[PDB]
Length: 233
Ligand SMILES: Nc1ncnc2c1ncn2[C@@H]1O[C@@H]2COP(=O)(O)O[C@H]2[C@H]1O
Ligand SMILES: [Mg+2]
Ligand SMILES: [Mg+2]
Image 1: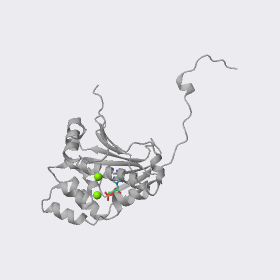
Image 2: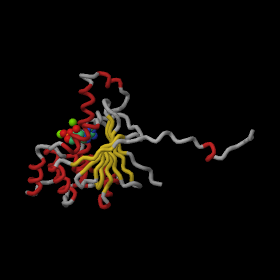
Image 3: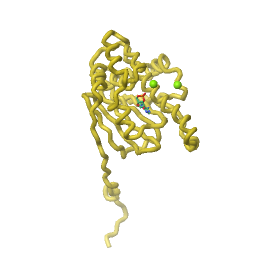
Image 4: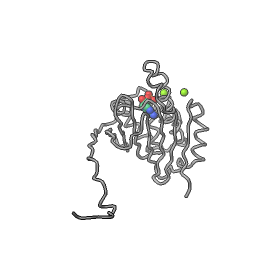
């Protein structure tokens, strides 16, 4: 009744998909973890570059788990995903992302493994730091992940395990973290740790620096690692 030969883009713009709800929960760090994070963030250390070794070690442990889980669950052999790590600096956003195709984490794994449960070595490690230990000793005390706060003001962890949905963990320290369901970009099995770098820590976006610290500290990953470099415009 109202003939048309051509429409403007706004006229044929599709209706939005239904808005999704994401459930968010907020948790306090275990008291000694909170102490540790306050000590890490607010103290000068000479050797901050070991954060990357700690996050790559976590990824390598998650990748090893794939191989062994196949002994009680052979279907993982059928995945076509390569077992690998990618490092992804974004100079536009000032973030460094460590991506793996390991086993991932469930929601309860994020809550229990990344903040609420005591690590037995945490008090000993804070005393070793007081007595002048090098921050590099952190992984030997079972709290390596929190080294990310040597260089990052905020950390976001996106993760997907076969036995659960995709979740995001996030914390800017200050004593709390959040876990929420993540209905955004499905990432497939594995974990992405997104470091929001502090203003004076932007050297960890540079490709030569990243290659230097991988070669110095992470030579026995056991899986291919790949550094994605944004082409300079
Ligand atoms: N990349 C990752 N993939 C899977 N789990 C992780 C990752 N990073 C940290 N974690 C979990 O966080 C925990 C930190 O302490 P652990 O190294 O004992 O065990 C670690 C894993 O359970
Ligand atoms: Mg370990
Ligand atoms: Mg190994």
